[PDB]
C-alpha cells in the first residue's frame, strides 16, 4: 500500500504479528515524508537493519504517491552495529523512525530491494 511513514510502521507491526513475531515503535520522526529504519531481531542471537530504498521519485512524487520499497542496511550483525548506524543516520536526518521487530522471517512482513522476491 502507498501510505505515510507513521502509517507504514503501525501496519508493519500487524504484518509481523500475522507471522507470529513481535514489533514496537522505538524512535519517531516525520509522519508523512520520514525515513524508516527497522531492526529484525533473530532469536539465534543476531540482528538486521533495514532502511528506505533508492526510490525512482520523479522530483519526490513517489515518496507519498508510490509504495517506496525498503532495503537491508545490515544483516547477521549485533545490536551495537544497529545503534552505530542509527547514530550516523540520526545525525544527518533525525526524521527516521526505528521499529524493533522480533522474528525469524522478513519477506512476508517487510519487502526489500536487497533481499530476493518470494
Image (tube, helix red, strand yellow):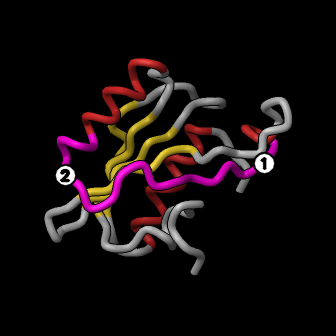
Residue 33 is left or right of residue 71, and the answer is right
Q: Residue at x 42, y 28 (%)?
A: 89
Quarter where residue 47 is shown: bottom left
Which residue has dot 2 on it? 78
Quarter where residue 81 is shown: top left
Quadrant (top left, top right, bottom left, bottom right) of the C terminus: bottom right
Q: Residue at x 33, y 59 (%)?
A: 75
Residue 115 in picture, x, y percent from top left: 51, 67
Specify start and end residues of the magenta stretch as a single range.
Answer: 65-82
The question of residue 83 being in magenta is answered with no
Which residue has dot 1 on it? 66
* Above or below for 113 versus 98: below
* Above or below for 85 versus 105: above
Residue 70 in picture, x, y percent from top left: 56, 52
Q: Residue at x 18, y 68 (%)?
A: 43
Q: CA distance from mark 1 to mark 2?
A: 32 Å
Residue 44 in picture, x, y percent from top left: 16, 71
Residue 106 is left or right of residue 111, and the answer is left
Estimate how packed mark 2 is, as few (under 14), some (14 to 19) or many (20 or more) residues with alpha carbons within 10 Å.
some
Quarter where residue 20 is shown: bottom left
Q: Judging from the image, what secondary structure is the residue with disc 1 in?
A: loop
Amino acid at each position: 500500500m502507498r501510505l505515510k511513514s507513521e502509517m507504514f510502521v503501525s501496519a508493519l507491526i500487524r504484518r509481523v504479528f500475522a507471522a507470529g513475531g513481535f514489533a514496537a515503535v522505538e524512535k519517531k520522526g516525520a509522519e508523512a515524508a520520514g525515513a524508516i529504519f527497522v531492526r529484525q531481531r533473530l532469536r539465534d542471537g543476531r540482528e538486521n537493519l533495514y532502511g528506505p530504498a533508492p526510490q525512482s521519485f520523479a522530483d519526490d512524487e513517489d515518496i507519498m504517491r508510490a509504495e517506496r520499497r525498503f532495503e537491508t542496511r545490515l544483516a547477521g550483525v549485533e545490536g551495537e552495529e544497529i545503534a552505530a548506524l542509527l547514530e550516523r543516520e540520526r545525525r544527518f536526518d533525525s526524521d527516521l523512525w526505528v521499529v524493533e521487530i522480533e522474528t525469524d522471517e522478513i519477506g512476508t512482513l517487510l519487502t526489500l530491494v536487497d533481499q530476493p522476491q518470494a
